[PDB]
Image (cartoon, rainbow, N blue to C red):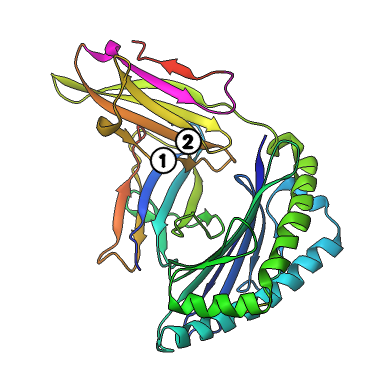
Amino acid sequence: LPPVVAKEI
Amino acid sequence: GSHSMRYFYTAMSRPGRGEPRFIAVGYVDDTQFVRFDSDAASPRTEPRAPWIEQEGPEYWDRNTQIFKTNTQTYRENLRIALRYYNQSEAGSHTWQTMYGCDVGPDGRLLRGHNQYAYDGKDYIALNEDLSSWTAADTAAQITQRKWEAAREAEQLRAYLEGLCVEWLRRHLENGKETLQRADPPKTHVTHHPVSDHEATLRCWALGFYPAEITLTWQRDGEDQTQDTELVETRPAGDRTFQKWAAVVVPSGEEQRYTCHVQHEGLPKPLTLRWEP
Amino acid sequence: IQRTPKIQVYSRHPAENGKSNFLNCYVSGFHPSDIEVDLLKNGERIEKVEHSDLSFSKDWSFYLLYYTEFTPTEKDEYACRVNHVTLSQPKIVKWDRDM
């Protein structure tokens, strides 16, 4: 499974 | 024998031409197995390697859910970046991210990766301890304190040490026939006269996998680094790669030259010479 | 910033006139990602040309492989034409059976 990028810079 | 799973995300703004495009691809070593493109008619994660196809619909829909979320998060990152760098909304910009876990022969994590680049420039990266960050500039420092405050590194650590390596081990098992098979390079030396006093000796390596390889020319046991022409390893299109190293030698002296080939698919380092 | 692409034109298998093969144009080391690539046959553009999914190297530069099935001959000339924001005019690279 691909990593979740839920947090913005 | 040391393997890795990697995901590469690219998000690009294009003012006046719709919302930013988001593209994601996944690899196991040098084999791509998945892709996602927000620009596709009906955006959905698609298989790019035979062995992954057997995964159930749960896997695929979960993938699409993650990528659609990532698509919106990166559109926000593009908007946020304009503020961090005092840039106009009229220009096109790029965000790139790499995630990955390297595993050793026994399947345990050798190390995890997570790096970001804005417009092709390093921005922020998770350190090897998978607990801290390294910011490249003052804008990235903002992101760093922001991520430290939300303990993002801890969630990433869990993924890298958990899911990443578990799925990599699973992919390696299902795609064993190819992922765990090294294909040695087919090698030969060609001769091309350039002048009456000189000629080009080209050492070829074809049909090999993985891409990692070493090709060097030696003149009487001495490496000709500075005088060797080496082209970037290139994909053949059938999963294998190609590469060559050439050297211009004085006519008659070619026997003082030997081509050395190192590849994990070879029992031992090869040594070649032009055979007229 | 901006990086101009490197170009390599070559076939999948050693070329043998008459034998079906695959013509490749591999572009790498470029940034930004927008790029136009055409495979040429005697100056004209081949219509059915496919390409790999956008990806990039550790230095963040992008790479793509454009390919088309083809049967090399003695006289047919093949080439790759690339255009990128770093290029004033399209760059053309001829296919050399020995490269």
Q: Which of C36 and C53 is in front in this view?
A: C53
Looking at the rendering, the stretch of residues picked out in magenta corresponds to B253-267
Q: Position of residue C58 (x, y in %)?
A: 49, 54
Residue B25 found in image quarter:
bottom right
Residue A5 position (above or below residue B7)? below
Q: Is residue B200 left or right of residue B106?
A: left
Q: Which amino acid does label 2 sit on?
A: Gln
Q: What residue type is labelled 1?
A: Tyr
Badge 1: residue crowd in 10 Å (few <14, some 14–19, many ≥20): many
Q: Which of B129 and B252 is in front in this view?
A: B129
Labelled disc at residue B242: 2
Chain identity of mark 2: B
Q: Position of residue B136 (x, y in %)?
A: 45, 69
Q: Which residue is drawn at 64% across and 60% down?
A: B130
Q: In which quarter of the image is the C terminus of chain B?
A: top left
Q: Position of residue B91 (x, y in %)?
A: 40, 83
Q: Name the residue under label 1.
A: C10
